[PDB]
Each structure stands twice: as structure tokens, then as C-alpha cells.
Amino acid sequence: AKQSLDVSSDRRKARKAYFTAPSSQRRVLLSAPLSKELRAQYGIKALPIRRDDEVLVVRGSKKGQEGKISSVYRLKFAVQVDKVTKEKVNGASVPINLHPSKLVITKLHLDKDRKALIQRKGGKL
Amino acid sequence: SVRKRKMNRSSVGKATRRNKDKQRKINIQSNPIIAANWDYSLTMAQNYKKLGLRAKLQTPAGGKETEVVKKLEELASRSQSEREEEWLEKLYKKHGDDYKKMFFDKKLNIYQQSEGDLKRRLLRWKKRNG
Amino acid sequence: VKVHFDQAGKKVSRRNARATRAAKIAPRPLDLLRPVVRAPTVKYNRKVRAGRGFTLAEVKAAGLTAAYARTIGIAVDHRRQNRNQEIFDANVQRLKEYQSKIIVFPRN
Amino acid sequence: SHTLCNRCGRRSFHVQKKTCSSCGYPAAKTRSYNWGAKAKRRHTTGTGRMRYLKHVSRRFKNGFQTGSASK
RNA sequence: GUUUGACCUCAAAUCAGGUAGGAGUACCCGCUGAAUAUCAAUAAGCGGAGGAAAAGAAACCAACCGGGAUUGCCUUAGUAACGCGAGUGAAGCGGCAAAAGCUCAAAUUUGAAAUCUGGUACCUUCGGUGCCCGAGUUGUAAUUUGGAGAGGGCACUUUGGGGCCGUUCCUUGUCUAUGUUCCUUGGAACAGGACGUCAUAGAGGGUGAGAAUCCCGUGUGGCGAGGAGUGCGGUUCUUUGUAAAGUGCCUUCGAAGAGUCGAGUUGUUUGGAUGCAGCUCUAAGUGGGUGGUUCCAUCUAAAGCUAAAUAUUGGCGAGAGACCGAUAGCGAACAGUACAGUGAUGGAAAGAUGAAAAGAACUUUGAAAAGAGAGUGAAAAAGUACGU
RNA sequence: CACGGACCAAGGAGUCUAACGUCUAUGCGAGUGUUUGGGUGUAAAACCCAUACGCGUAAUUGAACGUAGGUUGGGG
RNA sequence: AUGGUGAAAACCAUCUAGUACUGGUUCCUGCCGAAGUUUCCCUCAGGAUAGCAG
RNA sequence: CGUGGAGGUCAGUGACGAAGCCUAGACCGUAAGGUCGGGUCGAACGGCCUCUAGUGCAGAUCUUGGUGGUAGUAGCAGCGAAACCACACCAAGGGGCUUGGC
RNA sequence: AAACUUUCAACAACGGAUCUCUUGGUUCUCGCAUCGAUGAAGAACGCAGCGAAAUGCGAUACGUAAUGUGAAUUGCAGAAUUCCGUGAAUCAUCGAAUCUUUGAACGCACGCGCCCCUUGCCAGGGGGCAUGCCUGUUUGAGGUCAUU
Ligand SMILES: [Zn+2]
């Protein structure tokens, strides 16, 4: 149960905030858990996802598929995975929109900011 | 109201302020001894009783010294100007301890100080110097 | 038509204000010592009640001055006269007890 | 009978009377009445751009601070 | 002086330093104000402020063994009182919330207008200093505001300013637990069963259908960064000057709001007979105001300031509802928009596809409507005229 | 006679408030009413009451001399 | 009535959801169930009383 | 009897289909209604003791929205309404039920 | 008889009535005071590559300046990025600028003047000149007093 008087459990307010959340907040929203093998390595449960991050599919019809991410659709709250695409009747290939919460990161992309964030979140490298 | 709807529709964004929790919490800011012993878990009356102090002097409405020793222990925790000293020395040399004679000194007692004030100042000077 | 839905809210606000005063006024008891008073209107004269402040005569008899008494938490009322020896004695005893129970920290 | 009004552009500026019945032009005060609750709402503050009033609330939250971030 | 100076008065300057309109308006203050008693100090109109406004420390309430700023609630009380008819309708005392007292006029600083605005150069810049300029004597500072107070003498008591770090408050970032294990179905498991883990965290939201353990989040604490201030604990430099106050005693003095109170009359309000308001007159200092059986009780009006408990359908920001659910709820869930009126003004109708557009590739009949095949899709008995 | 009725989906009306009463139920009982407030609190929730206050407890001055009344009926 | 509009008799927004007889008054079942009148406040206005039914 | 909402209980029902709707299907009750058989539908709803009310429609020349005869008519091969709409030839008895007929 | 009037089972059209839900409305409670000549509210014109409404912006025009986040935005084209980096977002914060014409609206009015200055008779370029009143400086005029 919530004890703070500054936090509201109203369904309407939470729904409005989620849909109207800015891209900066949506970045935090679009988190993805790390693989159990990676969790032991970095000692961290989840981190924000990005383009070069490699992720695995754990739910949906594409369960078991993996590939490098190519775009993070913050507006639609969806992310795209390379080689995970649909086949239209006309032959055009359209990437399938997936939610990061249903995917497991298999190989992170390491930058200075990501390294700093890992240390900040109690991780190790 | 129209303005509220405009603000909600505007992209500027609300100036959110979350301070509801801070109303319940108040930190003591008038004593160092109380702050160390005060417990925010208890109420004002309960905290005063725990410290051993009275939170009300008049009969309160409705139904109802290990720390005071520190407060009691806490209870156990001017000269003359150079020109004033010179003026006192001049009169002392000219009249010594003759306060009555010193009172009537027209050209050294520029300010007509009383005998009591003169003797008190001279005694203070003697105690400070000799 | 006004409905006192805020009664609980008003009580909470009053309690919060009292707590804030205590935080600012921690060492002191938030109240000024008041004298005993006998009411007019014989229907109520039997009842004794607290007054606004002690009279100048009572403060003088208590061994302190009104100006100094105010800084120690004693309410002073120069409008009330004295015409009862028992009430004067009770007020003097209360002031003496207050002086014997108060602790004043050094200004140094 | 009426014409565009510079202050409001409501096309209520009387040609012969040389006055606007809506906003009260050229009178300094803006015409408004309590009984005209809908009229007040139509011209109440917030219906326009609010170029300056919008940022007052944000500025107050910071205590009207001045300078720049220390980085 | 067949002149030259002191002021006072009146004008001007693209003078230097300043402020005023108006907007909003739920609450506040004043004026005015309808549909002889009633709707009524309401509706409407005008002027003036803030986060509250007004009021506020008695020429008070009481006739008691007296209470002692103002304000709000209960009680007093539907009582007293009135219009005694319909009806209007108080206030003291009592209990509660919160409490804070002060500043001028008044009697010589005359052994020193000791006061203050502005210009100039610096510094430690919401200000300080040296100098100058001007205001002030037709009174600027200290000393006194009835609780009295002031000039002296006698035993005594006391004392402030600026920086630093902490402290508190505001803004703001971050760290802080556990499955996505097995089986059944499903397009999707967030559904059922089994096996497990965290819980000061089973409030809430998203994730192809009801998720603590997928994520965002929440409980408790830690770590930061930017501002306020002296509400205070240390830290550091300074005081000073025959400087300012307090205590008890002795001594010499000891001011108090006039076209104001009051009476008369005329308009006005009150359920009060009070008060408000044009005008003739116009009061006294052991004086004046308010109350009763010879008067006795209580204050000192004709000046002003002051947080608190008090209102709040406007503004900003938050926590909630035994509330309503697209013919309801604000007129407006996608609008004060389209639209009508020369105008003041009136003023609507309209929510949902599908997990995702994967929005019907392609063949084929039609100048054009869209048809027939074909396929996508859980479903097209979901085809953008799309939740049923 | 007349008033309304072309048909259908939705909408639609003795509801709320203040005072004064009867009846019924509950609590206490010559006492009663916590909630104007104060304390407390897992927080508009939940639990207690110091002082006052409304009602009644008695009045044609005062009522015990006795079933705070003899007799006759009177559920029992 | 208040405040405005245009025009060389009206219109706009509130007091006003006002001033009372036309119309309507929404689910089922069971039991009981009258009257159109006494006559007092004389009478148009109606109250209180009297009868029926609880 | 029925409905909106709330406290409690069914360790209730439900993608192996909750609600609504349809149904020349059946069961239960004197009825308000409940229940089950079959089709569309898709994600919430119900058995029971209480509390709560913006709680039940056949009309108010009732409000919103929708659709018919009038009528393919008046009217301007084609376009195309409005008023009105409880219902539709007469003899006698009785205002348009009794006995009969063009 | 056919045709046509009428009752019903099925099929085919209207409309969104019933059921489910909402970035909504309404009501209750709490913290604070925050418009303007240093130019308020409001109105008109323009600005995104493509633009109806909304929002933002003012010729520095769906933004410019500064700090935080760290790899986007997205209906289409277009951009890149050294993306191990003083650095993209239509992101957040927001203290520094710009801030078109009107509008208390402020040069004079019911078109249209003046100080200034400048880079080249004459002009581009830049800021101001509205009314009521308070303090100070400058100038001018007029009543009292003095003038051996
Ligand atoms: Zn105008």
C-alpha cells in the first residue's frame, strides 16, 4: 500500500500521465530486463534500451527470435528488432512493433554514458 | 474554467509542486538538545512528556528528569575608555580619595558627575589597574 | 448554505499549525501563564476561569516586572483591577510556582 | 451600420456613433457586465495566446531567479 | 538707490530620479440601488485592495466576591425586543480556536537641526562610507503615550555588528526485492493447476485478454546539485564611548485630538430606538461619555499601525468521491468551433476499426459509383459508412 | 361530446432541506446528548472526554399524619 | 425591474425554476374499504365540529 | 418482482466465451420476473443479508434521434414535397352493439 | 387463376438503441499568492519541407541563449554521426535574448510632424517625443523687506 500523500493511485491520472508522458519519460518507460547471464555479469536487472542493443523475444508469435534493434518508437511505445519483419501481400517488408517489456537484452551497446549509468545503478563492468 | 482548460491544452506544462507529505513532517529548529532527543514518531504532547516538559499551561480541553538535567546543566555553560581612564587618573592624582573636593574641581570635572558615579568609576579603575 | 465538510480538514490544519509552532517554539510550552478569574453574572460567579493576563500589582507582588515577565511567558493585563485578597493570593502563588519551575537558557 | 474594430475586430464598431458595443472602444475600460455571463466567458482571460501570463506561474515556482546554471 | 540683493508666489524643460490608469473579480471595503410594512441594505451599476480583506488593543461589557484587543463556532436563542397580525429578530455572561502590543499631538537638544532626500568616487551593493547639493526652525532626530511620565541623588544589574560551516525551508537528479520455471487452452497467457521467492514494497498504470515477482512504479532509508534566510549550534574579526537601558529607595515636577461633543431640524437604516447625512447654533477641564436608585460603577472619544484563529464557485499546484457515464456529466470527452443575427447576443451535432494497417498486392466489368474473383487478417457475421 | 394519440429507440416526473408532531425500534434513565472542540490516529477513516450548554427532574408561597390515601370495583 | 443594442416602436442577458387552473403522474399481488352529509364557526372563502372507514 | 451504486459472503462465474441482442424452444410462479435449449457478439458479470436512489412509462397538442401512408402525388423523359394520419357504401332499432342489403 | 391487399419463418437495407470502456465532466478536501508603461488581458498578419484544428513562435519567427538526460524524430521526403561524444529530441528544466501591427496604447489627428545619429543637395542605419501627480536641477516673471 502507498503511504506517501504526494502520490495518487487514481486510474484516470495515471492513464493520462502514461499517454501524455514526454519522450524523456518514455525513455525510462521503455525499459527491458537483462538476460540472467547478463544479470550476473553486470549485477543489474534492467537498463534502458537503445538502437545497437541486442534483444531476444520471449513473448508473442515471434518467441525465440533475436536480432539487433534498429529503432525505438517512443511515440508508439514500441521498438523494432532487425530480421523481425512482416511480409505484406505486395512483398513490402515492414518491421513488427514489439514492446521492450516483453524482450530480454542479450548484448548491450557500451558507451561512456551507458558505462556511467551502469556504475550509478550499482552495476559492474 | 477557460484558463484551466487552456493551461491543460498548452504545451508549456504545469509547474508541479509536491509538498503534501512535508506538511506532516516538521523538524525542530529552535533547540539542539530537543532535536537529538525529539522523536517524530510521537505527537507534540507525547514528545513533550517523553522529554519531561509541559506542552500546555492551562487546563487542556477534552480528555488526555533524565533529559531536563541536560537543560539545567546548559545554564552553567565592560571596561573604561582610554580617554575615560585618563580623565579618572587626572582627578585621582589631583584629589586622591577626596570625593567631595573632586566634585568641585571646575577645570578637571568637566562633566558634573555625582560623588557616587565618580567613586564607582574610580573603584572600577583601581580594580582594573590598581 | 454552508456545510462544514472541512471539519476534519480544519482540525488537521490546526494540529499542523500547532506542530509548526512547537517546532519553532520547541523550548517554550506555546502558552502564556494566565491568572485565575472569578466571573460576573452570579449564575456563573461560582465558576473560576483563566484570565487574559496578570495585573500589574500581582506581577509586582510576584517579584518581577511586566516587561521582564512577558519575555518569560507571563500574560500581563493592565486593564484588570484587584478587589479580592483570595484571588490575588492565588495568582501570586501561581506566579511563584511558574517562576520556580521555569528554566531560562543563558543569552551568551 | 457596424464596422471592424481595431481592439477586437468583432465588426461591432458603429459608424455613426464611432463606438464598439462589444468591447466598449474607444473607452479605456473593456465593456463587460455581470448579467452577461456568456459574454464574459467569450472574452475572459485565457481565450487568447497569453504570451506573458503563461510563464508567470513557472517563474514564481523558481522565485523569479536570475542568472544562469553553474554547470 | 533714475540701483543691487533676501526671500515668497507663479510658469516653463523632448531636464534627472519616480508613481497613476487597465485587466481579473468567488471572498473583501465604500457609494448607489428596483421589480408606507414584505421580497431588500437582495438583483443590477460604479469606484478601491490582498492572499485573504475589514476590525483590532475600549469615552467596552456589566451592577457582579466583577470580566479586560479584534475575529470565527456552539450556547445564549427562536429568548429579550419590535411589528403583537401575517412576521423580523439581537447582544453580555459561559465553553471552544488562536493570542502581541504599540506609534504621534501634547511640558526646551538650545552647552551646539544633533534629522533627512539627492549628486559624486569607492567597497564587503535589497546597502555603507568622505565630500557636496537641497529640505528642515511655520520643527527634522532621541527622550513620554496615562500601565503614567520627566530633571536630579543613593546601592546595584545588563549590553551589540559583520563573514564561514552546519541546521531548517524551496527547486531538483539519482541508488535502493523477488519466475517470466513446468503442464492445459488461446492469435496473443496478463486465464486454471504444480513448483518457488520479496513484502516498512499485494496503492496504481503499461506489456497481442484479470500480472507483486516483464517494466514503469510504491515502503524505508543514502547519495547528490542550485537558491532563501538568520528560526539557532559552533566557527572568526570587532567592540568603548566618561555610550544606552533596567531594578529598589529619596527628592523636584507632572501635557492629554473644537466647527469637535452636544441640542434642533430635515432625508436614510434598524425587528434595535441607535447610528449614518444637508444645515442655524455650538460645549468644559479635579472636565467629558456610558448605566440606577442622594448620587455610585467603568473608561478617557473627536489620530494611526499591528501576524494568528475568519471567507474563498477566480489563479497556480496537489489528495479523493456509496457522483454522472456520449440523449448523462460543464453548452463543449472529438466548442465558445461551425453557424444565425447591421448589432448587443444566441449557439449546436459529433467518442470507440483492427494486437498491430497486416488499410484488400494482383486479375477482371465499368467516362463514374463501386462490383466479381484473389488474398491479408482470430474473425472482413471487424473493410477506414470500421468494438455489438 | 371534447383533450391527446402516424409509428419506434433513448430521456421524463411526491426527490432534498429547516422547524414542529404521532407511531414503531434501540441505548440510558432522573439522568441524558463523545464528534462547537481537545486528545489520539493504520488519517475526512477508527477510539476517548475537561469545562460549559438544551431538556426534564416540582410549584396552587410548598405539598409525610397514612400505599408520601380510607372505602368500592379492578389483570393477577 | 436592472444594464445594454439599433432605429431620425422593438430587441438582447439576469431578478424569474415568479404570479394556478388545462394536461401527465411509471412494477405485481392480497386484505379492509365509505361518502356525496350532520351543522357550529352565519353565508362566496374556508377552517373546526358531526357521521362512515382505521 | 426489477435496476444504478456501496459493506459483507459465495478461496463464485468467464477466451474450453462474462454482458447485451435474437429466438413459430422449454421450465418455474396468480404476477412483477427468474431460469435453461440454439445463432451473432466479444471481457466483464452474477447466487444471498443489509445500506443507498437521478430506481420501473402508454400518452403530458412531452424532449432528442430515427422511419412509414400521404406520394413517385401537388409541384418544377428526369427532380420532387407539405398539411394530415386511433381506425374504415348504405336501410331500420340504437354517438360511426342488434338485424340486412349494393 | 394470375396480378394485387394482409399475418408470419428466413434472407437483404436504415439507426446506433442494449452491453463494455474512456487523456471527460461534476462534487469534496489540502499547500501557496503568481497580471501591467522594464508595456497586462484581448484582436489582426506571418513562421514547420509537405498543414485542416490545437499548441508554440515574432523577420533570431512550431524558435535563438544556458543546464540535465544520453542516440533520436516519424503520416511521407529529407538529416546524418565519429553516436566512447561540450551532443541529435516536436525531451525536460529554463534564470539569458529576440519579441511583427494593434490593443491601458503612449508623436499630432480624425493620413502623419520633431531630437538624435550615422555609413555614403539628399538618404539608409538606431532609440524616443501620450496625459494626472511626488522628490531634485535649470531658466523666466511678479508681492514683501533691505539699499548713505
Ligand atoms: Zn471592439
Image: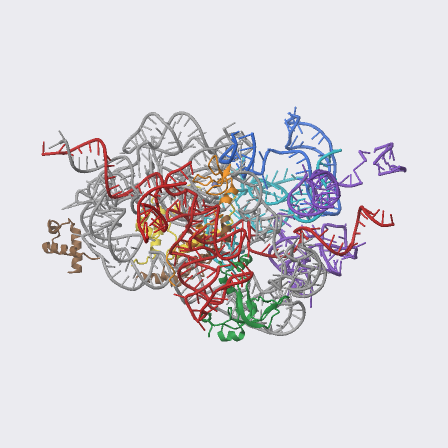
Chain colours: A green, B brown, C yellow, D orange, F cyan, G blue, H purple, I red
- For the residue pair C32 and A33, the one nearer the viewer reads as A33
Point 46% across, 74% down: residue: A124
Residue B71 is situated, as x and y percent measured from the top left of the image, at: 35, 61
Tell me: residue B70, above or below residue I1. below
Tell me: residue A100, above or below residue I97. below
Tell me: residue I74, above or below residue A62. above
Residue D56 is situated, as x and y percent measured from the top left of the image, at: 43, 52
- For the residue pair F44 and C91, the one nearer the viewer reads as F44
Residue C25 is situated, as x and y percent measured from the top left of the image, at: 38, 55
Locate residue F24 relative to residue H97 in the image: left or right. left
Residue C86 visible in the picture: no
> Splitting the image into 4 quarters, where does residue I134 fall?
top left
- For the residue pair A69 and F5, the one nearer the viewer reads as A69
Task: Check the picture and name the quadrant holding the C terminus of chain C.
Answer: bottom left
> Splitting the image into 4 quarters, where does residue H68 fall?
top right
- For the residue pair B45 and A76, the one nearer the viewer reads as A76
Q: How many marks are shown on the rendered structure?
A: 0
Residue F47 is situated, as x and y percent measured from the top left of the image, at: 53, 56
Point 33% across, 44% down: residue: C78
Locate residue B126 relative to residue C103 in the image: left or right. left
